[PDB]
Amino acid sequence: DGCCSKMGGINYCDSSAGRLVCNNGFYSTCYCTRHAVMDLQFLMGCCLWHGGVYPQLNSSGLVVCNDGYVSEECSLQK
Amino acid sequence: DGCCSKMGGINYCDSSAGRLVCNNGFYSTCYCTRHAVMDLQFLMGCCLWHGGVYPQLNSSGLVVCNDGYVSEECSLQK
Amino acid sequence: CFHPPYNNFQPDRRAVKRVGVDTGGGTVGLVASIYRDSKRKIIRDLQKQDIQYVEYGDTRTLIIPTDKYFMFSSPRLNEICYPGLNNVIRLLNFYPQSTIYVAGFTDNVGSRSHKRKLSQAQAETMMTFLWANGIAAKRLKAEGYGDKNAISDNAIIHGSAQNRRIEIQWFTS
Amino acid sequence: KETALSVGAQAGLAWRAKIIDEQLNKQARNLDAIYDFNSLVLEHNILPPVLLEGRNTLNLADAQSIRISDRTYKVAKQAHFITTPPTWRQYLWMDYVKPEAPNVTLLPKTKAEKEIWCIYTERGWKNGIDQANTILEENIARIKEDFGGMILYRKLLAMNMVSPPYVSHTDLGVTGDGSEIHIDDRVLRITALPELNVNSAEWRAAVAK
Amino acid sequence: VPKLPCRVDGACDATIIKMMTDLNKKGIKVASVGQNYLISIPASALFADQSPRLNWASYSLLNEIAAFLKQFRKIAITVTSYSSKYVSVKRERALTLARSRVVSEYLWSQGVDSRIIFTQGLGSDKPITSYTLGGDRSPNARVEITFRRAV
Amino acid sequence: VPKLPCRVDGACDATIIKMMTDLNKKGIKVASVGQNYLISIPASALFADQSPRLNWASYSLLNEIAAFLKQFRKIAITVTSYSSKYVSVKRERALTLARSRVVSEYLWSQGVDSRIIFTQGLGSDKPITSYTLGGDRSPNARVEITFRRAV
Amino acid sequence: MKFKKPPINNPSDDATIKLAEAAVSVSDSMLEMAKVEKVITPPSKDNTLTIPNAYNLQARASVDWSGPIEELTARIAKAAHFRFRVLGKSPSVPVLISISTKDESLAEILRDIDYQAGKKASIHVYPNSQVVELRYAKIY
Amino acid sequence: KFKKPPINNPSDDATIKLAEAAVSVSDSMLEMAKVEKVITPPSKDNTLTIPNAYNLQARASVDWSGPIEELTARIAKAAHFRFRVLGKSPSVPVLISISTKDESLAEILRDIDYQAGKKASIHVYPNSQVVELRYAK
Amino acid sequence: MYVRTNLTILSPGWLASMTSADGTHAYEMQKSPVLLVSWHGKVMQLKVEGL
């Protein structure tokens, strides 16, 4: 909520930096573009390190990845 | 709207210049003819710098210029 | 009373005006004069302006922004921000012994020869402006470098803005 | 609601279009300063052709097969006649039509409807901002590629990598019947398009001091 | 037509006659005949004695002059500088040239809607009043601007 | 935004500047210019008299410096020690090297977000105050950490 | 006891940022290729030999212009009190030039005009005869 | 009193970067043309100058576009000078096109020779009041 | 499109051109609502309605 907390305030968003600038000349620690450097190391989804989810839908709950490897963690159990 | 204010009032519209002439012998800065010299830098419409809009109406939301290019900003999106 | 064009190169008589308008009150005028002539107030006003002051050890440095304090792309010096320059002269009056080195910096864009000449022109202008306020000519040395030792990144925009500057260093003894 | 975020996307796209067109109109002189096509033309009112570079090429076609090369170059668009030099407005002035007709099929009647209308219209507004910026980035990359191709042809011709274009001009005297006449007949045709020369022995070096 | 530009930007002939009436009753000469427009100023309201330096109050008059000349649409501006006979030919010619240079530079720095600026300084070679008692206090020492209004 | 990181973890510029003020009122020099930053520390509140042994009370200030240093995103940190001449060249050089080494050791032991750290010590070969009345108590004996903050 | 960096001004715009980012690369490419062109091809002479200065040509001029050469050079000549002369038939393709300069010599302005013109045309000055002559190219 | 700043000023970092880039590219293209332009020397250019004969200083107006020889013959008759030709007229005529409202005959002949170029030239002699059209080989 | 003025057009690039004795230009060009000219050294945008 507070980017330039105890500081002046937002001047602009440098998209080369992907970051805001405070009224004082320090590089503000606040994201403004999605094209910044986020060191995210946890992820989401299914069929990762594979071809992704195959676009078909099945009568069964069995969902395969696009490279052909099956995924029991995404396919529902019985 | 009264262009020859604080002067003699309007005499006529010299359309050789496309400018109003007042009863005072000075050139009025208002224009009165379409065939007259403006100084404009902004335009409207889409499919510009091209053949204009294609005359036919595409069934989908796409619009296309006469040289074949498609203006996605004028076109309707999803 | 006071002239905007650098007061026509004369040391000012300001505290007399301050105590006169205080009487219009001598003691309160005197304490206001000494508080406004205090060094810390001058440094606070300098940092209220866009000028950076650095002291660490026996060496002191001043940082001036070229684009905000000059006409662009030319050694013509902008004089709209003259109160900062006047207070700079007031500060530099306090240290009448050590020599002063001044250097110029620009960014990495264009001919390196062009950067060198632009920095040298800025150095010459700052050199003669500091000389003309009354300090002796052999107390000064000026140099203008291009992008040799940048303290910022050229590729990022705010750092590219921060790179071009005027550096002033001086010792004590 | 989905139509509401759609019309919010429309409004945001048009608003960023107007803003970027004002900003681009603000810097008219420097664009013509930097994109001197009229200097970049050649002497016979001919557009120099377009070249593309490439360094350190590696391809793994499949197993047991690797093809590598150091550099390569590509003719993109062949040289041709031109009449007036192109300007930046032919590549950068993105179109704009303001939509002033939001037909609200789903009017708000509850404050919760007003609030979800606000948040989804905000989402559409941001999406329109992102789309406009993407469009601008695509256009500026395209025109940068064009200028780089022109400059690449000029310097490869400087380095003796391409033959210059060759033009034959034929001039004839008066012509026509007793009713229609043209007083002289000058016809220019380019018999040799520019192309690469594979004989590397004619190449020359380059130094700086 | 309402979408079309009805008049030029900031065009008001009431303001035009207001500022020219203020300048004429102030004393700086402004004359108009046909399309040709001349404005003359004495150097005593512009400089000090025999010196190409600007006093800080003069920028108000410079702003008024710029506001007047930006009102019209034009192509070429010609300014010229005239001096008294003080020492020589070289010194007076260079002083006139420098004064024309600095006023042209300030005018281009301000928002002038013109494309050509011409400066020329002469000195004391085209006088007006043969009465030549004063120095820079003389009315002959002057600076003139001129243009033709374009359409 | 509900899944994308809105901020870098543990980022608070108010915390940054309040501990900057607290450090400078503690008397540890903090220098900020460009993207380069310097933290300079007197050795008297850190070590023993010409001895490479940490005092126990110094670990609170070391924890403070680590808490400040973990805030930014760095790549490389450089630390260098300086002292006064007491015996020779070699003893002073090795003492500076050992002091910088143990400081770097505890700093790597804490979770600093750096990839590269360099440690160095130069004895007394860079005096910053010609007034050299004291020895270890003189303020020219020092330790400096330095980095450049990027992106 | 506040802290700030020196450069602070009005806020920027992302399109201008991307424009500058492209323009830096374009500029350095043009710089290095100007260097390699100058190295591999040596000059021979100077156009200041053909266009010498003279007195009353030292009037200062600041000029912005983006049109054909004709009326621009004509107003230059009528400022110079010289004789405007045209040599060769006018080309079918119009000749266009662009100038954005600040307070230069008239003679240097002329040399800049001819340098921007290149192979299409040439300028000669006969100051004894007070004649400014232009001439088109003899090709086609 | 007051001193307003320059109104159209690049007060922004992007703007000043753009402006100095524009300076660089303008300078680079300028020196490119400077080092690539070919210029004839003024002491060796092969064009005909003004002979300063008094009878050639008269003024006229000609809008002609055709062959060269009859035009030169009528020009010589207007100058009351004699006319000579050397060489052979080729099959394709040498073509010229001069449109002017007020000009003198000396620079008329100068631009005639300039439009002639290589295949023909002209000489003018004031000792014996003659003009001569010379073909090439 | 066929156009007649006494200025010089720039933007689309024409196919055919013709010039009077007095200095009037006429052109034959591909259809477009936009024109660019240099009026008297000033760049000028010219608007066409009716296509």
Image: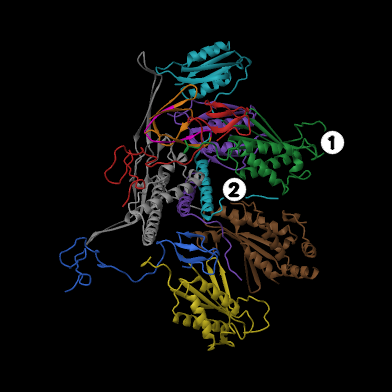
Chain colours: A blue, B red, C brown, E green, F yellow, G purple, H cyan, I orange
Mark 2 falls on what kind of element?
Answer: loop
Q: Position of residue F22 (x, y in %)?
A: 57, 77
Q: Is residue E77 found left or right of F111 in the rendered image?
A: right
Q: Residue furthest right?
A: E133
Instruction: Write down the region rendered in magenta.
Output: I26-40
Q: Is residue A48 found left or right of E53 in the rendered image?
A: left
Residue at the (48%, 62%) spot, across then down = A20
Whether residue F7 is in magenta: the answer is no
Residue A45 seen: yes
Residue ID for mark 2: H7
Q: Amino acid at mark 2?
A: Ile
1 and 2 marks on the same chain: no
Label 1, label 2: how far apart the Cα atoms are: 41 Å
Residue at the (44%, 48%) spot, across then down = D18
Image quadrant where one finds the N terminus of chain D: bottom left
Mark linked to residue E133: 1
Mark 1 falls on what kind of element?
Answer: loop
Q: How many marks?
A: 2
Q: Amino acid at mark 1?
A: Leu
Q: Chain of mark 2?
A: H
Q: Chain of mark 1?
A: E
Name which quarter of the figure residue B62 lies in: top left
Residue at the (77%, 42%) spot, across then down = E44
Q: From what the image shows, is residue F46 above or below residue H130?
A: below
Q: Residue furthest front?
A: D109
